[PDB]
Length: 300
Length: 300
Ligand SMILES: O=[N+]([O-])c1ccc2nn[nH]c2c1
Ligand SMILES: O=[N+]([O-])c1ccc2nn[nH]c2c1
Image (tube, rainbow over all chains, first blue to last red):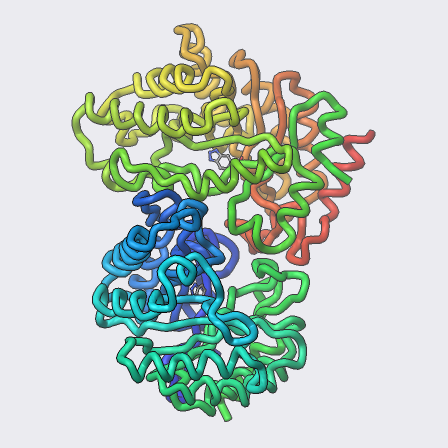
């Protein structure tokens, strides 16, 4: 059975997966995505280092391939990350002038979003903006533009494509008692109360064995910020226990504003942490017990 | 135990593999390439659709990543394919003017080769130019420019980087009695007699089970064209029988002008024909029997 179909039958929008051109032309990835998943995200092809490796020199071939494949196969598309220190080329982080950085950031956002205007359901606009203690991470954007870079990014994104749902994303939001989780919720509440157009919080969910249960409490806390949507993104679980995966799915089901879940690849050998076999299909492209456990949960 | 080291000890240049950025950041590919392979090729990142998606506007992010990684890790680099109908964007195949297409082709060759001048051992300049009956394939280049497109491509490439070995590549050159095999020999002999700088013939070797034995006769026939080098490229073998792989390796060893062998990926799940499990490492990144058989053959 298709986990995307089953999650839609439970009132959710999608079960998604990260992919890119050379996954779609190898292995069994295309067949599995066509049958079992409802939304695709670019694993790498929309990051800043992939799309604007030198100023104004945009590289869209990989992203274009993904968008076209998704449209021809009737899949939703997520995009990102527009503003993320981790995939930033050196030409950006060397800028020290506030006006120039504001305009470089705006141009990067606008160019990417305009190119795919109307085709992208979700954009991850700002990623990993928080330190573990809940303060704002001191990236080039914070240091040079100041704390208004987040309002600016979201206002710019809403203008570039008013159809898209605009998300902030972060990791280590998996426990309700962790300071980072409470910090992002209270900042998003205040931003939205001042009119910043943050439509969603996306939780980059990279779990160790046994950590799925904590998401059942963390995700309702993220939803308390009052955004229209929340999502689980980049999901993988070391060991791929059925218990951990089913707990994450049930957290999604329990939270009315949680629109769906995206797993960070199809098959274990193509994972960034392949030795932890953390995905739902094995190296032979066979569904693993965690896949079947999700199916059986969603049927009930 | 490294098949590249062992083939170098037998007097050859390399045992190589095709890869690209998102293979190097996932799985165990980087570790295996570091330990066991001596040359890397771009699986996709130097093809025309990837590098020049609109006229004169070049995308280098993916290819730059691979070249940098190879230099950091002491590996040789192959590049290609500069002129190949199978990865051609639509803007090229809609040109009908001979001068314009000639200039477009020359600019594509010169721009890529200049960017990496001195860093690339081998360039595959022209690919898949022959029909199965040995006539020239009627691609946009043949239809618009005529058969001079092949001489022009090679002369342009030699001027752009005189350090690089320049190859023509084709597939189905695996049997000495197949018409295509003798046809490429006939034409390469004629082009070299006219001063065209074709340094190598690269045989894109996609075998079915039991076809390795025929390479023992086909590869010496390809070498009879008199090029300084020949190579085995894009190698994969359905079923990955040790006998097939060893026969291909011994064909290389038997042909003085054969500089090396490149396999078309690391692990089975990442193959274009993964269901045929045709590579040297399995879906758990373990070396398969064919890998160990190559090790023993190179020591014997
Ligand atoms: O959910 N995702 O797998 C995913 C992948 C890449 C991304 N970049 N930004 N947001 C992303 C989400
Ligand atoms: O040998 N190769 O694997 C390989 C891969 C891609 C290519 N493009 N042109 N030549 C190529 C060789």
